[PDB]
Length: 109
Image 1 (tube, rainbow, N blue to C red):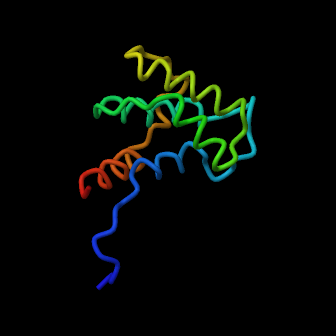
Image 2: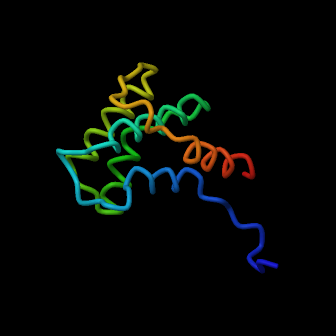
């Protein structure tokens, strides 16, 4: 009994949560959240959902991200939407839990 009729699991917006992170104070020096973000982003692309760089900048302005980070992500989304591929600096950091989390929200959608 949730009472809320139906509702909708915000899968895509929870992906933004991973992109924004739990520490939004970062710009030039990003650690794992550069390549892991790419991993998640390319997973969406693999599912057939190529994100537009616009939605990154737009949501970045809304949630208050750092421009340098947003522009980098926009460059990734650029290539992602264009159908290109990017290099991951640390492939081990793409953990299964994050993937199956998004996957589960899309599944129940």
